[PDB]
Image: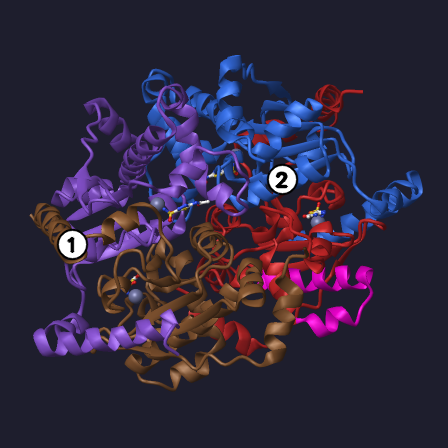
Chain colours: A red, B blue, C purple, D brown
Amino acid sequence: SDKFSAALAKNKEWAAKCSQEHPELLPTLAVGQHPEILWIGCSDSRCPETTILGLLPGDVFTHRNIANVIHPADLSSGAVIEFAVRHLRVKHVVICGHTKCGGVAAALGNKGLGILDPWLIPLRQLREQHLAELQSLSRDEAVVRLAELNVKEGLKALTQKSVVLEAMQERGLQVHGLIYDVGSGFLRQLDAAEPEEALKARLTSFKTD
Amino acid sequence: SLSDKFSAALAKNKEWAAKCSQEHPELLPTLAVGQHPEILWIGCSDSRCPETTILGLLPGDVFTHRNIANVIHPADLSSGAVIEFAVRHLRVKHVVICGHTKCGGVAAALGNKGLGILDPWLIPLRQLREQHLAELQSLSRDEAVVRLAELNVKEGLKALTQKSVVLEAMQERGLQVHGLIYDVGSGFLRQLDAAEPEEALKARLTSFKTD
Amino acid sequence: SLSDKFSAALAKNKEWAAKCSQEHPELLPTLAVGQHPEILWIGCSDSRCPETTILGLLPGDVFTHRNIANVIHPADLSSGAVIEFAVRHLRVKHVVICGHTKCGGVAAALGNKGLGILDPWLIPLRQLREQHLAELQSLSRDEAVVRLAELNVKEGLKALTQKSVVLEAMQERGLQVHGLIYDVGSGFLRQLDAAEPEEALKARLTSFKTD
Amino acid sequence: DKFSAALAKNKEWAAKCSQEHPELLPTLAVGQHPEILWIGCSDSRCPETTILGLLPGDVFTHRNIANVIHPADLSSGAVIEFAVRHLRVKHVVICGHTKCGGVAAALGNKGLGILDPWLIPLRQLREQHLAELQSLSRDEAVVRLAELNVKEGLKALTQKSVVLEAMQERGLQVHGLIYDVGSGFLRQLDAAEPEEALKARLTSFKTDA
Ligand SMILES: CC(=O)Nc1nnc(S(N)(=O)=O)s1
Ligand SMILES: CC(=O)Nc1nnc(S(N)(=O)=O)s1
Ligand SMILES: CC(=O)Nc1nnc(S(N)(=O)=O)s1
Ligand SMILES: CC(=O)Nc1nnc(S(N)(=O)=O)s1
Ligand SMILES: [Zn+2]
Ligand SMILES: [Zn+2]
Ligand SMILES: [Zn+2]
Ligand SMILES: [Zn+2]
């Protein structure tokens, strides 16, 4: 069965249902978006943000990439963060990793993957830093642990951006780390504690005028 | 409201997980064994274009990349890595590039306001604006936004087919590529005609196919 | 030891520092006060194209960026940051893009061997190969390398003039841009004619100059 | 006109070079075999071939603002891959310099447009070493951050499989230098890392055969 032609038919059925059951929603969204959440998650087909959050179109500004990696100088994630934080003024930035992330699993192996190798470098940087801890775990346990370390490192890379530090001080922007369990459907919050003195050093080092 | 949208979203997630356990208890545990999506979706980050919702599909159906204005920069590692993985490893049957009506990324490229880090990101849209300037200036402002959104999807399909991994999959298994526009006002997807002369793809094969 | 090129280079550095102190004792201390180069050079990393040597110039004269095959990716931060700094802050009067004969980067783009991380880097040369394929196929292999090297310089000058900082400097203070080919066999630089129809530069100004 | 003057000086240099090293340019035309890859600053005061007292063909060169190695940068990535795997250079040199205004800009808090994402790695080092940098004078902090940047660059360089392979297979060496723009001297940084550091890097980054 052609999944593309099947998807177009299901789109038309969904759009007609939306007109019947929430007739104001799509026309009000056409006037302009006002999402309160920026979601940075994995491209993994099992992590569709709006479905797993039980939300609607217009609720979640979304960036998805392999293993939800934030490269500090990546223009793709950089442009979405600039737009979502400065222009849409989202109240929340969520970084969501997930269980059974094959990107994280690839980083724990040493098989050459072409253009994927430079993309996964930040996961291999965390692997080197945390090697003794990761080697003490089973492969399945290491995949969860490195997925968590990657979310926490992402929150650090996110808060190293002046536009985020500005929004946190000016209008109480909040940032959050999650792990999605692909087997249960539950989001879990990471404790993601950093000393107060961590954000002070970051403000000094990264906030610009 | 007075409601924290983050804590409200976690509560709704638990309600959705409860519904999955009650109505389709096999689905999430079978997906945890491994994904097998047949579709790679490259679309806009715009909150109004959630691919799995608007396609009426489930988790596991759509491998997804979303960025500002669904732009494919040829040497971007972010889109590059997702295309390599989806095409070579997951062996998707379809790559969809979906633009949308009222794309403010496309609209920003038709303006000349300095937007900081967004300026280098939108360069491919300004390249299309320069190439098609006479055509775009002959339209109304709102028609030029729709037209540039279409040209951007078509240019994205060209950038996509400049990748050896995609040309190989098109030859080896008839991987298909599709250009769509999402109408944020109606919820309908429409297909772009997106024909290219045969001699276009032959020159591309010669110029970009790699061992 | 005596065959180590690195320890030999450090010894030659100390000999060069001694020569500077003996022959031009004011030069290095006056440069330490601040640089004022009038030229930004964008050239190939090729060991045969050291800009300051081949121009017969001194330290402080040439602000320099060198990469594989002197390629300007429009959204590359590495070349982007050097252009912003050289044009807006140092206020260079000249931006030079220098290609060269026997550029193996240009030759690699005319081949179809997979080269790992070099593949995405060379995409702009394969874009030119696809656009100019009939012309390149009508030439010998060696002539196609020279022609693609020239097209690459000219395309770089286009990418350079798509940047508002360059367009601003050209309009406000007569910044000039130049395309060169370095002949690695003779040591001579030759200028490329690099003329563009008037309507080309007007569309670029409209599409890329910031308000 | 500095540009037309430079083209005239080029022609004079090429004619002189045919007299003084009559066969050098012709040997160069048949191919290049440099033994050194130089990664340095774009600063007009740091021309590698001049300050090393070397000739064309001796130094494969990459220069960027503040000699920064972004791990997933294709520009520096492509030159390292080509120089190490194809030319088989014996030495990779990362050269920082005194009075580097790129390093100085990272110690400031002015917004600089497209320069901001480029300088993030220097601001990462500033945050990590902030107590040490704040304890120094302005001019001493610039020298210190320039040194930390070279050392961090050598770490990013050795996180690349192509470099780790060459070090193991053929004793490729990597070196950190600071160029003094006022004296003309290169000095070597001690750049010591525990043995356990390079073992974790090999485990985390070297691609399987
Ligand atoms: C090599 C590689 O990237 N493998 C992946 N496996 N799953 C991935 S996911 N969770 O990003 O879809 S990526
Ligand atoms: C400056 C800029 O990028 N503006 C945008 N407006 N909407 C965008 S969208 N459709 O990508 O959400 S981007
Ligand atoms: C594979 C590849 O890139 N080959 C090269 N040959 N010479 C180059 S040069 N002129 O940039 O040094 S690049
Ligand atoms: C803001 C900025 O980049 N300023 C610079 N000053 N000197 C530089 S150098 N040493 O790279 O030429 S960069
Ligand atoms: Zn994943
Ligand atoms: Zn959009
Ligand atoms: Zn070259
Ligand atoms: Zn410098």
Q: Mark 1 and mark 2: span between their CA atoms?
A: 48 Å
Q: Residues within 10 Å of mark 2 (few under 14, many from 20)?
A: many
Identify the magenta region.
A130-155
Q: Mark 2 lies on which chain?
A: B
Residue B144 in magenta? no
What residue does disc 1 label? D17
Disc 2 Cβ-to-ligand 1 distance below 8 Å: no
Residue A150 in magenta? yes
- Quarter of the picture containing the C terminus of chain B is top right
Q: Is mark 2 on a helix, strand or loop?
A: helix
Looking at the image, which residue is at 28% across and 80% down? Answer: D139
Q: Which chain carries label 1?
A: D
Q: Name the kind of residue labelled 1 in the image.
A: Cys
Q: Name the kind of residue labelled 2 in the image.
A: Glu
Query: In the rendered view, would you say B131 is above or below C171?
Result: above
Looking at the image, which residue is at 43% across and 75% down? Answer: D148
Looking at the image, which residue is at 30% across and 41% down? Answer: C163
Which x, y percent locates residue D97? Answer: 30, 71
Res. A203 visible in picture: no
